[PDB]
Amino acid sequence: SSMILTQFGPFIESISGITDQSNDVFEDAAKAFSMFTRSDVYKALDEIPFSDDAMLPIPPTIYTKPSHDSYYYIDALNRVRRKTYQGPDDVYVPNCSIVELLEPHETLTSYGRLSEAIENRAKDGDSQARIATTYGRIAESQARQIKAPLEKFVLALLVAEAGGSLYDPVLQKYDEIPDLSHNCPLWCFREICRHISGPLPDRAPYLYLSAGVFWLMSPRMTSAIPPLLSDLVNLAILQQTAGLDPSLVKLGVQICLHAAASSSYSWFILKTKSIFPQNTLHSMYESLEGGYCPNLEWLEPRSDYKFMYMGVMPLSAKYARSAPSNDKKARELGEKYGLSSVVGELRKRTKTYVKHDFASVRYIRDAMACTSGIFLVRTPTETVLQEYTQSPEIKVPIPQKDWTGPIGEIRILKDTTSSIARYLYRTWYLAAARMAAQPRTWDPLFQAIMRSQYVTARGGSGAALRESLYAINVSLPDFKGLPVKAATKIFQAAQLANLPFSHTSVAILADTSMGLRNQVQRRPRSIMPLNVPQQQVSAPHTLTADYINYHMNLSPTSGSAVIEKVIPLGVYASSPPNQSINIDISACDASITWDFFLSVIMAAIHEGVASSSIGKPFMGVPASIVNDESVVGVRAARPISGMQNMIQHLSKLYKRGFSYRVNDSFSPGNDFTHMTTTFPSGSTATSTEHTANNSTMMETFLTVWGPEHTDDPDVLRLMKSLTIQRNYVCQGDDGLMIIDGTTAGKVNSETIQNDLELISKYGEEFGWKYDIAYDGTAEYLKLYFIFGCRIPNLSRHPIVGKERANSSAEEPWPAILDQIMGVFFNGVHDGLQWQRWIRYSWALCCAFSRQRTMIGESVGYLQYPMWSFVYWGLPLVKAFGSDPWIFSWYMPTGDLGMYSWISLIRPLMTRWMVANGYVTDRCSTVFGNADYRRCFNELKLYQGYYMAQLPRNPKKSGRAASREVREQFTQALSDYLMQNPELKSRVLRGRSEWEKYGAGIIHNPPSLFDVPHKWYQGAQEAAIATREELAEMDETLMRARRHSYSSFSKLLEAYLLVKWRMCEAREPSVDLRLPLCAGIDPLNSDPFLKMVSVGPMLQSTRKYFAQTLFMAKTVSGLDVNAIDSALLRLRTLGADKKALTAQLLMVGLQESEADALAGKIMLQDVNTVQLARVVNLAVPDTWMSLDFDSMFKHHVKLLPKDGRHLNTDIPPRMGWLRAILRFLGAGMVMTATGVAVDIYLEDIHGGGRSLGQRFMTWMRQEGR
RNA sequence: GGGGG
RNA sequence: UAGCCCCC
Ligand SMILES: Nc1ccn([C@@H]2O[C@H](COP(=O)(O)OP(=O)(O)OP(=O)(O)O)C[C@H]2O)c(=O)n1
Ligand SMILES: Nc1ccn([C@@H]2O[C@H](COP(=O)(O)OP(=O)(O)OP(=O)(O)O)C[C@H]2O)c(=O)n1
Ligand SMILES: Nc1ccn([C@@H]2O[C@H](COP(=O)(O)OP(=O)(O)OP(=O)(O)O)C[C@H]2O)c(=O)n1
Ligand SMILES: [Mn+2]
Ligand SMILES: [Mn+2]
């Protein structure tokens, strides 16, 4: 460690709280990181005096592996395939030798790539050559699922840990996290690699590059080493930063060693991934003596997902695990995969926890951080053949006799059907009618928003559409000469803009291109990039599904994103007396087929939508005639609406199936079109659709089936007390059945077990295999809960991991920084040990802050000052002679955050600056007599500040665009959007109205007329950048670094005029013995103190924020937050109502709605959060898990502590100031380490009035 | 672009 | 060729 100490000495102390941070040391540390050679990191690793406890037997078979050749074969269709041995799952990358297939690299003679000879033979068509190429390309792919070379993360860890234990400012003692000599993962990493390199001078087992992966030419290297090493590094970092129990961590290493010792690392990982969760989380408290859990009340209406904390629920034996024991299956699993030693140890330790508390949840969390974090990989061919093959077993089909004769592509489900489909059909029919009945549905704007949803910069099987169209002699415009990417639905929209639906209808049946996605702890999933006409025609399906979800059930719309996964719901559901069943449906997409679901859904919508859609087109789709054969004998023609025409065309596609075009670039010669009946993922209907069926069937079970299939009084009573509107929350195929508890305790476990078994049997009737789980735990949207405590899963957030489905190279340098910041933010949300995590993050950041640049022998270097990271959100450890660790990771981002940390030490800074020569006679309002301008330019604080705000990726705008084709394109886009003259007429009105009442007040008027331009830009910025555009990006960053400044942004200079007084610590908002988030306990002072004093966010963040906008949606391309900001700004700038009415007309509203919302906005008392947007202030993401609403309202006093001040008084017409002022106070409170404190407005330099004018100038100048 | 179903 | 839905 002397090697590390010498090279990063001063920097190490700067990030350990011992010495101040300085850009000079930081940049040198950066240069040192870049000058360190890979092999040096290993040499550094050798310098570590590892303890015996950090060692464990390493399997010799991890090095000696068979040839890959017996693991593959050519199938009947000539595709290269993986040959199974351990089951139908054994389709991943096998653990084999690989050096025999490599050619030494010219220069790195010890490293090699796949023999060019072998690929050439493979390309010629040689079976053996193809097999070898496939293996080589997929093994390479497996090794690319990381963000950057492992050595960088390791070096970072060495540098960070060289600082020793950290002194907690709050607890006033050093932490007791074992040093690296006790880190088993690192030891293994060094040994495994050393053993591989053997006598070779090169210590790296492989090199992650841009030109591709290269393997160390050693007979001991295996295709399984990259994944193994990647798991070890994560575990190594986590043991030091999450303060994980070392003994547990070793268990995680053993599993990984076993995975590398097996015949397939990924496969083995997939089969054993439940070990830690099953033997801890799902086995906790078989016995229970005490502890406390939350006591929440679910407010009304439950749909708001709003809860209120009511105290603590004392625990006792009464609440011990009552759910069935998983011991047997868990042990069988361990025995089957050679891990019974691990399962047994976990089972034993889990039993020792008889109290539910911080210690016990941290144990679970720790255990669950040890699961491999690799993104499983297998060839595309394998994913497609495993996911689009299995078909649902409909044990009780809809009788053929129950369908009427056809009505085009659909058949009505006779109302005399005794089938359970009866209910599924009624729900979709009902919702279809109500949806189509809504007036908004027939508003040109609404239909523009819908037509604009799928017009995006992402793909849409562009090539297949062009050819399915060529098949009927219809050639689309090619716009020869435009600098935009052609494979975008945006390009598609422009091509189709001026063609009647009848000419593009065939495209609805065009093939579907391949799209893949790798996941952690899961298998790769195939994706279907539907084309514009396919997405268009899917509208009715999507809208009806949305209507069901908004009006008929209890569901959360989104994908996930911590807190957006409604944390509050899990706390409630998992807290005794309450209990929850974690319902999930396997093979969801493959279970939604025409045989039972789609034929019924298509029918119900087609019919229920009839009367209100009659005699009318929809979203560009015309009405038409179709053959009618409903009645027997009677055969006529039937007029249907455009909406019905859509269902008509969509039904034709759902019936036939999807032609998936598979071009497997990892498997030479594996080109085939696979037909499948599995439901599309890339469809706008997918998510909402599955959510709707989920609740609909659960409703039918609880209302009909269940009751009719049992006479058991308790079960009948239990089911009767459950409602899909009050007790069942779902999204897609995930479900959470919440059984509220009584004073008599919780509902009988045996009665619950009966209900579940019936649900299970119930789904077999229509092809659904319910994955039900009753284990005393709550699991929803990959969020884990036990006894009201959230258990972050560190396993799913691989520090070094990064999904990479395609072969394309990683984005140019700059890009990596956003990823590193994301790694930091995940740690904040996962609750790692704040100091250890912050210090490590500074090391990591420093190690990626420098890049070598080229301009033609013009070898320079791009360096980001430490200050850029602060701007991005990374808190300072110690600066300007301040105490160490005074800054919390809840410090805001950007200007708000800069304001916060600077205000907390304004005086320290001023004093430091003067005592170091930065003095002047001019007395600064913020920094007194400190020559701040000279200081900030020299320290690179201004530089870093501005560099952080520059594009971290090449720009394509400015590419020579031949004006004529450029106008044709944007015209096509315009016609697509402005199809309906009514809409256009609306915007033109807003326009001339704007010139009279709004023009001049603000300069950011959002307008539908901009969309075509924003769409063009999007298609542009989607294309591959050139090396020139790259240089241009660097030059920009480098010019900002050279330039010298005299101030911060106009908004930051304005906030700095405001001063506060931090006062009394707040009282606890929740009980301090209450486990809310594992890892967030008295051992993690700042996070814990913030959680306790500020309080947890007990409402859904989606619901909360939906109340901070006047309009929820708008045409894709415009920014809802932008529209909201313009309206409020106009109001704040004294604009007349007619001006807001004009703004609203320009974004598509009818004059009546426009005038109404405008008049409504004028007289409204706007909330802190919504109002703060007038100046671009947003609630920080890191704050989302806390009760920031309460902080703004009751703990940021705008009235000075000692009464009113002339400067602090808020002018009559400037009440909007209070919202901005609330954010600034909150900033300082949240940025200060420790307990949330009450803060009092102390001063505003030039007074409130002048402050307001200052903000009003910023407002009216945006976009000039 | 980032983090997540 | 590389989809859809969400927090900044
Ligand atoms: N990028 C993504 C990720 C997920 N999904 C959707 O999420 C839904 C279900 O999620 P999973 O549980 O992850 O998919 P399953 O096929 O059901 O996996 P298996 O039963 O193992 O869980 C269906 C799928 O289309 C999606 O459209 N796009
Ligand atoms: N002032 C410097 C010089 C080099 N590098 C880093 O070095 C790496 C590759 O170049 P080297 O071959 O390692 O640089 P050398 O200067 O030739 O090595 P040193 O003096 O020991 O010889 C990439 C580049 O960013 C750097 O960050 N800053
Ligand atoms: N913004 C960037 C990114 C990369 N390059 C050029 O790309 C070439 C090699 O790519 P890298 O592998 O990304 O650069 P290295 O210095 O070899 O190391 P890495 O980015 O970790 O620093 C050399 C470098 O000048 C550049 O000029 N400007
Ligand atoms: Mn599922
Ligand atoms: Mn699921």
Image (cartoon, coloured by chain):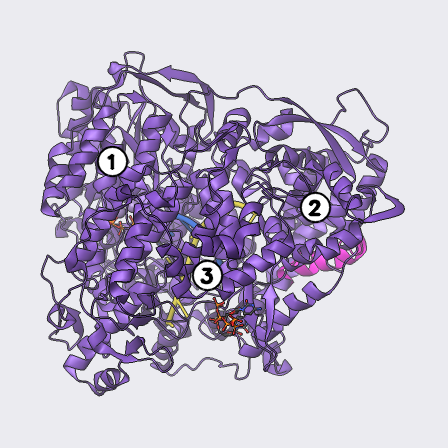
Chain colours: A purple, B blue, C yellow
SS state under label 3: loop
Side of A275 where A477 appears, left or right: right
Which residues are drawn in magenta? A987-1009
Amino acid under disc 2: Val
The mark nearer the N terminus, 3 or 1, is 3
Q: Which residue is drawn at 84% across and 31% down?
A: A1207
- Dots 3, 1 in contact, CB < 8 A: no
Mark drawn on residue A700: 1
Q: In which quarter of the image is residue A515?
A: bottom left
The mark nearer the N terminus, 1 or 2, is 1
Q: Name the residue under label 3.
A: A454
- For mark 1, name the chain: A
Amino acid under disc 1: Thr
Crowding near the residue tagged with mark 2, few <14, some 14–19, many ≥20 C-alpha atoms within 10 Å = some
Q: Residue at x 38, y 37 (%)?
A: A552
Amino acid under disc 3: Tyr
Q: Residue A1008 lies in magenta, yes or no? A: yes
Q: Residue at x 48, y 63 (%)?
A: A456
Q: Name the residue under label 2.
A: A1175
Whole-percent x, y for residue A878 in the image: 61, 42
Side of A987 where A563 appears, left or right: left
